[PDB]
Length: 273
Length: 9
Length: 100
Image (tube, rainbow over all chains, first blue to last red; front, side, top):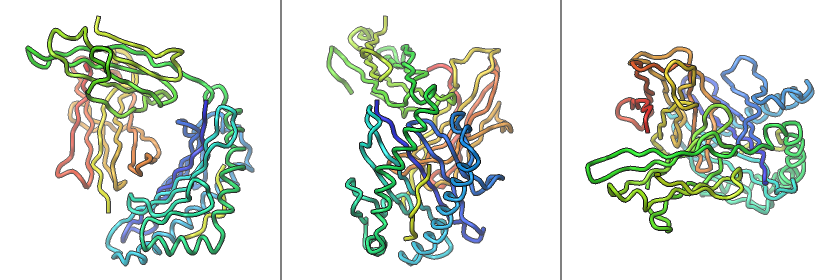
């Protein structure tokens, strides 16, 4: 199916505590493969997936050099943003950046993105056409004008539509054994009596990959609303998720749980029986 | 692999 | 300035079976800002050998972190995750409910 490569950067100023924290992590789909942590000992881009360790020293030195360049740019950004918003030096602020590319089942470019946020909110981002910017407010307009005049988008687009996709293909290849896998969810249901007239049915999905999945409850062959928890990581490269529904004691049979996942040839339908 | 040409705001 | 309170999930990597080594997870997500304190507790006492994932964030820019420790569940051992964040008046302690 489709695949993606994404880099996530987090920068946090630390008032009166020196240099800002800088964390960068790279992902291929839902699998992290590298990381850089300003507070870690190596001060280098590090591998976080087996298939990426096969990359030579030229790769690691190049990624280390580039991630450090990102860190430096973000270090300046924090000061600049504080000024744009005329905020005091007393408070910590956050800069976040995300960029990468999506490819279809044919491993060909599908979409690109480069988004930037300040204090947990959209600040500026490339439009899906990768040729113009969308600035969230008045302060961000200044950045938009600077980047348009310097033709930033052009170089970013070149990356997002080509280089990004090339590396993604490469990674999907080198990590075929893990990245190009699909682990169907292992499912089951639990039943717990709330009161003497009510019972909650929980539908479980475990050990699946990728994280994408749909768990829907139905009472009499029709969608119904139900608690749904966020898909959570198991810690072994697979994910988990559950959906519960409160049902009148003695009506369990009416309810059915439906599971959709790319690892399931055909959707699953579970019932308390 | 990381990109380049990332300028300051 | 956006503040998002953390969502907390405490669970095991594999179905729990007393006497069998497993991993205790504390997944904290949807929070902002990034500063957060996460500790796994064994009978009310902090576990030292706890690892955590690298800080990352979701589409809505909210952060998520997975804290985990290798452990062997028993019948008498009570586990929980203590989380403190600027959005919480007091540390939130979520017990590991083996059932569910």
